[PDB]
Image (tube, rainbow, N blue to C red):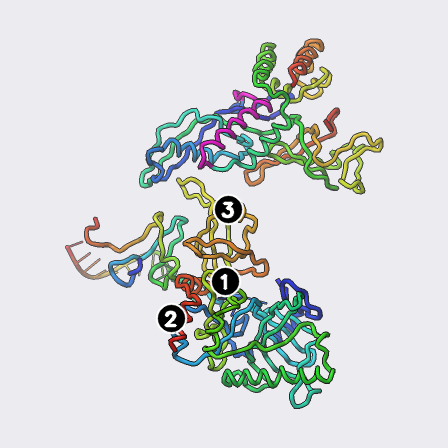
RNA sequence: GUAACCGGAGAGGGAACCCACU
C-alpha cells in the first residue's frame, strides 16, 4: 500500500470493514494508509497469480 | 457559540449579530490582512518538532511564553468603532476602549488592527481580564505589518501603550471604567528564555512561543513555533460513540475519534459509560500511550480541528520536545 | 402479557470466532442480538432462558460466514387490545399522565381520564385529584390501567391506554 | 380480531406458556446471578433492569413453592391457560371484581367457586 | 488549533451500416 498504484508491485484500492473504498492513486492522506487485520487490499496482479 | 471570555463576564463587551456591520468588519479585516480565504485572517502558529527547531539557528528570533488565553483580534477604526474578533471570525463590539492618537490626544485611532489575547490574570485574588499586544497588523492606513518585527513592537509601544497612559495621567481616561486592561506582551531574546527553563516558574508556565523577526504573514506561518510540554499535552475530537459490530461479528461499541475535513474515524478510544455523557460533542484528548484519552469537553467549539492539525499534533507528540531537550540545544549557541 | 415461547433465528458467525469454543460464541451472539430487542409481531423479548437447539451451520458459498439455525426459549411481552395490567406513574403533565409498564411506556390522555380527576398545577408535585380530594394520583404511584391501542416505533412498541373503565385506578 | 375478552390469539402464539410476575422475577434473578458470575460478559440491558425492578415491586409472593402450588391448584380446575396468570397477577378480592377485570370468567363459573378460588389466592399471598 | 476553500467531480448517449481481425 505504501508503494501504491504508481509503482507496479503495489495496490490500487484498500477496502475497509465498513465497505469504505480508498483510492490509492490520487493523493491518499497518510492517515488512511494505515490498515488493520479486517481490511481487504486490491493489489496488482503478481507472479504466481492464477 | 458567541462567548467573549469564558469564566469572567466583562461589562460593555457586546457580541454583534447585525449582518450589515458584521460583513463590513469581517471583509475589511480580510482587506487589512490581505487574507486569501475566509474566516480568521490572522497568523496561525504551528507546533514545534525536530524539523521546526532547526529554524531557530537559521535566523534570529524573539521569545515569549504562552499563557492561558483565547486568540482574539482587536480592530480599531474609530472612537466607538472597535470590533473584536476571535479565531472563529466572530465579532464583538466593545464600548469604553479609547485609543488616543499620539500627536493629537483628542484624536482617536482609525484603521488599526492589533493582535493579542484575552487572558484572565488573577491579581489580589480577583480575576482581571487583560489584553496582551504581541503584534500589530495595520495602523492608520500605514502598512506597519510589512515593517520589521522589532519596528512593529516599537510602534505598538509608542503609538498605543504610551498615549493611553498619557491620558490616564491627566485623568481624561479612567483605568477603572474600562472593561478590561490593555497591555503589550513582553518579548525577549532567545538567550533570556533559557532562564525560564533554576526555573522557579516551571509550574506557572504553559509553554513557549517563538516569533521570527520577519515580516507579518497571514494564516499558517511555518516558522512561528509554539513549544508545548509533552506531558502537558491535544486536539479537538468530534466523537460519535458507535455500536460498530460488523456482519458476522459480535456487536461492539467503540468511540470513533473524528477530525475536521476527514470523513473517516481518525482514531479510536476506549469508550466508557463515564465518557458517554458527551455524546456527539467536541472534546480534547491526550495521547500519552497509543491511546488517546479524554481530559476536558469543549462546549464552546463546535467543529473538530483540521486533518493537517491532527497530523502536526501527532508528529509533535511522537517526538516529545522537553525543556531539558531544548535547553542544551540553545545553550550550545 | 408475559409468556414463554420458543423462537427461531439464524446468526452469521465470522470465521475468526470458530476457535476452540464456537458454541459459546454462538450463545453469546444470540444473547447480544436478541436481548432487549423488540418486534411488533411478538413484542418485547425480555430474556432468553435457554437455547433449545443449535442446528448444523451452513458455510455460505463465496463468503466465510456461517449461519446457524437456532432454537431458543425466550420470555416475551406483547400487550393486548383488551388486557388490564397495573402500571406505575413516571410524569404528571397537563397533556396527560406518563406511566411506565415493564419496558414499555404508555400515556393516559385527559379526555380518557375521568372528569373527576381534576388537575392540580399548584400542588408542589403536580397531581391528579378529585373535588372530594379522596383519590390522589401523583408521581411514582402504582395504578390500574386499560391499554387499548399499541404502536410500533423504530421496531419498538409503545402503546396507549384508557382509564374510563370501572375499578380502574389507584391501587 | 385479537381480543383478550373473546380469546382470540395468534396461531403461532397460541401454544405459548404464560408466566407470573413472581416466576418471571425468579427467572430474571437467576439470569442476573448467572451474568454477575462468569465475568467478561455483556452488561445487562436497560430493558432487563426495568423488567427486573417492575417485577420486584410487583411480586405478589416470594416463595418458589407457592408458585407451583397456586399454578397446580388453579389448573386443576378447568380454565383457559391465559387466564391463570392474569388472575394471579391481578389478585381480585371479590368475584365481582374478578369478572369485571376479566370478562371471560363472567358466566364460566359460579360465584361461590370463583370466590373460593380467589380466597385461596389471597391465602397463598405472602 | 479559523466559517475544510468545492467534497479528487472520472459513468463518456444510443441505434444503424460498413470494413477488418482469429
Q: Nearer the viewer, residue B55 or D41?
A: B55
Residue tagged 2: B51
Quarter in which the C terminus of chain D is drawn: top right
Q: CA distance from mark 3 to mark 1?
A: 23 Å
SS category of the residue bearing label 2: loop
Q: Is residue D56 visible?
A: yes
Total marks placed: 3
Residue C93: percent from left, percent from top: 73, 41
Residue tagged 1: B305
Query: Quick check: B112 above or below C13?
Result: below
Tell me if B315 is positioned left or right of E5 in this view: left
Q: Chain of mark 3?
A: B
Query: Quick check: B173 above or below D102?
Result: below
Residue most extreme to the front: B198
Query: Quick check: B56 above or below B10?
Result: below
Q: Earlier in the sequence, mark 1 or mark 2?
A: 2
CB-based contact (under 8 Å), mark 2 and mark 3: no
Q: Nearer the viewer, residue D65 or B16?
A: D65
Q: Earlier in the sequence, mark 2 or mark 3?
A: 2
SS category of the residue bearing label 3: loop
Residue tagged 3: B272
Is D7 covered by the magenta stretch? no
Q: Residue at x 68, y 10 (%)?
A: D116
Which dot, 3 or 1, sits closer to the camera? 3
Q: Nearer the viewer, residue C91 or D99?
A: C91
Q: Chain of mark 1?
A: B
SS category of the residue bearing label 1: loop
Q: CA distance from mark 2 to mark 3?
A: 37 Å
Q: Based on the displayed image, in which of its 4 quarters is residue D114 positioned?
A: top right
Over which residues does the magenta segment extend?
D14-41
Q: Residue at x 33, y 50 (%)?
A: A40
Amino acid at each position: 500500500v505504501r508503494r501504491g498504484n504508481s509503482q507496479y508491485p503495489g495496490a490500487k484500492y484498500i477496502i475497509r470493514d465498513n465497505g469504505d473504498r480508498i483510492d490509492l492513486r490520487f493523493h491518499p492522506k497518510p492517515s488512511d494508509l494505515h490498515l488493520q487485520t479486517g481490511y481487504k487490499v486490491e493489489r496488482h496482479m503478481c507472479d504466481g497469480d492464477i | 457559540g458567541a462567548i467573549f471570555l469564558e469564566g469572567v463576564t466583562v461589562k460593555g463587551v457586546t457580541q454583534v449579530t447585525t449582518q450589515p456591520k458584521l460583513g463590513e468588519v469581517q471583509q475589511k479585516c480580510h482587506q487589512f490582512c490581505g487574507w486569501e480565504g475566509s474566516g480568521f485572517p490572522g497568523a496561525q502558529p504551528v507546533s514545534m518538532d525536530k524539523q521546526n527547531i532547526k529554524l531557530l539557528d537559521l535566523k534570529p528570533y524573539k521569545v515569549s511564553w504562552k499563557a492561558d488565553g483565547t486568540r482574539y483580534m482587536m480592530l480599531i477604526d474609530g472612537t466607538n468603532e472597535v470590533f473584536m474578533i476571535d479565531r472563529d471570525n466572530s465579532v464583538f463590539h466593545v464600548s469604553n476602549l479609547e485609543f488616543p492618537f499620539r500627536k493629537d490626544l483628542r484624536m482617536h485611532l482609525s484603521n488599526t488592527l492589533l493582535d493579542g489575547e484575552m487572558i484572565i490574570d488573577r491579581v489580589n485574588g480577583q480575576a482581571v481580564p487583560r489584553y496582551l499586544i504581541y503584534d500589530i497588523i495595520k495602523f492608520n492606513s500605514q502598512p506597519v505589518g510589512d515593517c520589521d518585527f522589532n519596528v512593529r513592537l516599537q510602534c505598538i509601544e509608542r503609538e498605543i501603550i504610551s498615549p493611553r497612559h498619557e491620558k490616564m495621567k491627566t485623568g481624561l481616561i479612567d483605568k477603572t471604567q474600562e472593561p478590561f486592561s490593555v497591555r503589550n506582551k513582553p518579548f525577549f531574546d532567545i538567550c533570556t528564555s533559557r532562564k525560564l527553563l533554576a526555573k522557579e516558574v516551571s509550574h506557572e508556565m504553559d509553554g513557549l512561543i517563538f516569533q521570527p523577526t520577519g515580516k507579518y504573514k497571514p494564516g499558517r506561518c511555518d516558522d512561528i513555533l509554539k513549544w508545548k510540554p509533552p506531558s502537558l499535552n491535544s486536539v479537538d475530537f468530534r466523537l460519535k460513540i458507535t455500536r460498530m459490530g460488523g456482519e458476522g461479528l459480535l456487536p461492539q461499541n467503540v468511540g470513533l475519534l473524528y477530525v475536521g475535513g476527514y470523513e473517516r474515524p481518525f482514531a479510536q478510544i476506549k469508550v466508557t459509560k463515564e465518557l458517554k455523557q458527551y455524546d456527539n460533542k467536541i472534546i480534547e484528548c491526550k495521547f500519552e500511550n497509543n491511546s488517546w484519552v479524554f481530559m476536558r469537553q469543549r462546549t464552546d467549539k463546535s467543529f473538530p480541528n483540521a486533518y493537517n492539525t491532527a497530523m502536526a499534533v501527532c508528529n509533535s507528540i511522537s517526538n516529545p520536545v522537553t525543556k531539558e531537550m531544548l535547553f542544551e540545544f540553545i545553550d550550545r549557541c | 402479557m408475559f409468556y414463554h415461547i420458543s423462537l427461531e433465528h439464524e446468526i452469521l458467525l465470522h470465521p475468526r470466532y470458530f476457535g476452540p469454543n464456537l458454541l459459546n460464541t454462538v450463545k453469546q451472539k444470540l444473547f447480544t442480538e436478541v436481548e432487549g430487542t423488540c418486534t411488533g409481531k411478538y413484542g418485547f423479548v425480555i430474556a432468553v432462558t435457554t437455547i433449545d437447539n443449535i442446528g448444523a451451520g451452513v458455510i455460505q458459498p463465496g463468503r466465510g460466514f456461517v449461519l446457524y439455525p437456532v432454537k431458543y426459549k425466550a420470555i416475551v411481552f406483547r400487550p393486548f387490545k383488551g388486557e388490564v395490567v397495573d402500571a406505575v406513574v413516571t410524569q404528571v403533565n397537563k397533556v396527560g399522565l406518563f406511566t411506565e409498564i415493564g419496558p414499555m411506556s404508555c400515556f393516559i390522555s385527559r379526555h380518557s381520564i375521568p372528569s373527576e380527576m381534576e388537575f392540580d398545577p399548584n400542588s408542589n408535585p403536580p397531581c391528579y385529584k378529585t373535588m372530594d380530594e379522596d383519590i390522589v394520583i401523583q408521581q411514582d404511584d402504582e395504578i390500574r390501567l386499560k391499554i387499548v391501542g399499541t404502536r410500533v416505533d423504530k421496531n419498538d412498541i409503545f402503546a396507549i391506554g384508557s382509564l374510563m373503565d370501572d375499578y380502574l385506578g389507584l391501587v | 380480531e385479537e381480543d383478550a375478552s373473546q380469546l382470540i390469539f395468534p396461531k403461532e402464539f397460541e401454544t405459548a406458556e404464560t408466566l407470573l410476575n413472581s416466576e418471571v422475577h425468579m427467572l430474571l434473578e437467576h439470569r442476573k446471578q448467572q451474568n454477575e458470575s462468569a465475568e467478561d460478559e455483556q452488561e445487562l440491558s436497560e430493558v432487563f433492569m426495568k423488567t427486573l425492578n417492575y417485577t420486584a415491586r410487583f411480586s405478589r409472593f416470594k416463595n418458589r413453592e407457592t408458585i407451583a402450588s397456586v399454578r397446580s391448584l388453579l389448573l386443576q380446575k378447568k380454565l383457559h391457560k391465559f387466564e391463570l396468570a392474569c388472575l394471579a397477577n391481578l389478585c381480585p378480592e371479590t368475584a365481582e371484581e374478578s369478572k369485571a377485570l376479566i370478562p371471560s370468567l363472567e358466566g364460566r363459573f359460579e360465584d361461590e367457586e370463583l370466590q373460593q378460588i380467589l380466597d385461596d389466592i389471597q391465602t397463598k399471598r405472602s
